[PDB]
Amino acid sequence: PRRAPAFPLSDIKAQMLFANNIKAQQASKRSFKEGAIETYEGLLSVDPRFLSFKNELSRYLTDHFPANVDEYGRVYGNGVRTNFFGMRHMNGFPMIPATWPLASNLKKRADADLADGPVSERDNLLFRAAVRLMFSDLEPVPLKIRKGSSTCIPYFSNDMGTKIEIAERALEKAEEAGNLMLQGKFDDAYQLHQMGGAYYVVYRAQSTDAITLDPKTGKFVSKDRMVADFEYAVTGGEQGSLFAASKDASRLKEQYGIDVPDGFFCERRRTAMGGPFALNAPIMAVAQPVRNKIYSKYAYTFHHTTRLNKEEKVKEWSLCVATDVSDHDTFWPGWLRDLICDELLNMGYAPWWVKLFETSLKLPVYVGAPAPEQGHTLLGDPSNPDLEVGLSSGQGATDLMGTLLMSITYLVMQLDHTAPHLNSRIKDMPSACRFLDSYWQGHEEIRQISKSDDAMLGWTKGRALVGGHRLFEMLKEGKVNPSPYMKISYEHGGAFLGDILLYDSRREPGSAIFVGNINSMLNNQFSPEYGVQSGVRDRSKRKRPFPGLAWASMKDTYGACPIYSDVLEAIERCWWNAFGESYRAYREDMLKRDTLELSRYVASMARQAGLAELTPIDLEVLADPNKLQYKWTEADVSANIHEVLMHGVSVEKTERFLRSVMPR
Ligand SMILES: [Mn+2]
C-alpha cells in the first residue's frame, strides 16, 4: 500500500535541505550522541553521589507512600499515582534504538479499527463547526518567536535578527509560495522561499518513564517501549519490525567507565520534529490569533491556568471522567487535515495559505540519528509532499490540530454513549455551529475541559448522567473502544494539565480538589529533560534559563499535595546522606544566583530587584520554558517576562499579512 521514498544524506534531495553554513551542515551529519547531562551547574546526572541519592529517595518514597488510586482510576488520600522509580534513569543516555517515524499511519489507524473519515454527517458537521468557530473573527497580533529556537530547514539559525528577517520575508512571500504549490511547483516554492523541504527529526528525552520493583526478587523492571525499524517506518508497518528498545544501562560501564547502580536504566527517547521556519511563520501568524480566540470566547473548555481555575469548573460536575489517548500524534488523522483545509476554503480563506497549511501536514521528514550507525535519511519526496505521519510536533499549529481533533472526538463520545437527545440540535452547519458554540462555553449539561490529548469530561445533573456512568463503566471494563476516531481509555490516576484531581471518601467532583503532582516536582528537580547549558552565554536562549527560580514557585505549585512536607524532608535526609550538604540551602543559593542573574535580562528590574512582581507561572516558565509549549500560553505570563523568552515581528507586518489570508 505504497512504501514512502527514502533518500540517503548523500542524495541531492537530502543535500538541498541543508544550507551552505556550519550549523546546517553539522545538523545534516550529526551522529548519534549520548552523554551525562549537567543536571545543575557542576553536577552530572551520573555523578555517583547523585545516583546513590536517587536510589535511596525513590525506594524510600515508594515504600512510605504507595499509590492511592481506586478501581476507577481516581486518586485519593496521599495524592500519589505510582511508585517514585521513574527517576531511576541515566539522564542523557537513551534507549537504543529510538523509533523511525512512520511515513504513513493509514494502516496503523485501520488495524486499530479507527475511522478513515467522519463516521456520520453529524460528526462531519461537528469537525467542520470546530474549524468555523476556531478560525472565524480573528484579531492580528505580533508573530512571537521563542529566543534561541532554530529555524531548522534549511538555515538552522538560532539568531533572533536572522529569524525576524526570515519571518518577515516569509510573510511577504507566503502568497507567491502558496500559489507555486497550487501549481504543484513545490521545489520552486522551496528553492525561492524555503517553504517546504522537510521536518528535521530530533530525538527528545522523556527523562522519566515507568519502572517497577518486582517483589519476588527485589529486581527492577523498566517499561518496554516499542520502536519501528527503518523498514517498518517506510512501509507504514506492512514490512519490517516493531520491537522493544534496549533500556539496559550495563553498556555504560564498558563504553564510558560509568558505574551503573542496580535498577538504573537508559532514558525513553521520543521523536520530535523541527519545522522549516519559512513555512511555519505564515502558519503561526494565523495560529496565535486562533489561540487568542479559543482561550477568550471558549475559555471554559480551552483556557486552563491554576489548579483553582480548573477546580471551579470540575466542582460543578456530577461526574468527571479523566480520559487517556493512546499515541495521539502518530494516530492523528490526515483526513482531518483535508477536512480542515476544505472547510477553511469554504470559509473564504486564501487558497494559497490553505495550500501552505495543507503542505505543512504532508511534509517529508529528515531522520537524524536514532542509534549508532543509523539515520541520516530523508523519508518522503519534497517535490511532492504526501506523507501521513500523523501530527508533526514542529508544525506551526500542532496544539490547535490536537485540540480540534480531541474536543470533537470527546463530544462525539458523550453524544454516542450518553446524550442521543442532543443529536436533533445538529441538523446543518448553522445549527452545528450554535450547538458547538454553546457546548464549548460550558452551557450544555455535557461538558469538557481539554488541551490536545489531555481532557476531563463532565456531566451535570442529568438525563445524560446515567449514560455518563455507563460510559465510565465501559472505560473501566476496557474491552470496547468508546470512539471510532482514536484509542480512548480512562487515565490511571486522573490528572489534568499536571494537576491531580484528588477525591475524598465520597468519590465525587463536588468534594474533589486539584493538587500539584508531587511526582512531577521530583521529575523536574532530579530528572530534567535538558542540561543547564552553562556554556550558552545568553540565558534566555537556554532550554532551562533560570533553573533556580523553580524553588520560589514550588510551594505554590506543589504545596497542596498531601505529602509535600514529607517529600521535602525525605529529600533533605537523602541529600545529606549522599552529599553531606543541605539540599534546601543548595536550592536557596541557586535561587539567589538566578534571581540576581534575571535582573540583567529584565529592563524593569533594578540591579537587585527581586521576584516580588512575578507570579508562580512566570517562575515555572523561566525555569522551564517548555511549559509555555504544552501547559500555558503568552497571556498567562507577565508581559515583562514574556519579552525575556520571546521576540516579535511587528503587528504592522502581521496585520497586512492577516488581511490577505482571511475572508473579506
Ligand atoms: Mn489527564
Image (cartoon, helix red, strand yellow):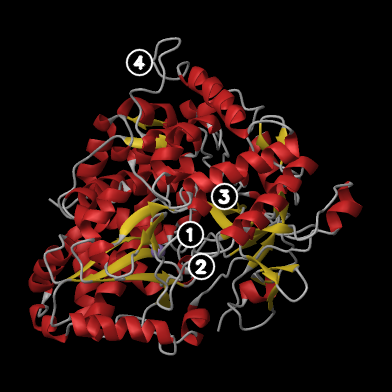
Q: Quick one: label 1 or label 4, which is nearer the N terminus? A: 1
- SS state under label 3: helix
Three-letter code, disc 3: Asn
The residue pinned by badge 4 equals: 604
Please name the residue that numbered disc 2 is placed on.
389
In the displayed structure image, the side of residue 639 where residue 132 appears, left or right: left
Q: Residue at x 36, y 86 (%)?
A: 474
Spatial separation of the CA atoms under disc 4 and disc 2: 45 Å
Q: How far apart are marks 4 and 3 (CA)?
A: 32 Å
Q: In terms of image quadrants, where is residue 430? A: bottom left
Q: Residue 523 carries which label?
A: 3
Which amino acid type corresponds to the residue marked 4 in the rendered image?
Answer: Ser
Q: Nearer the viewer, residue 271 or 276?
A: 271
Could you tell me how far apart the alpha carbons at marks 3 and 1 are, in whole angstroms?
25 Å
Nearest the viewer among 589 and 287 is: 589
Q: Residue furthest bottom?
A: 479
Residue 438 percent location from the top left of the image: 11, 65
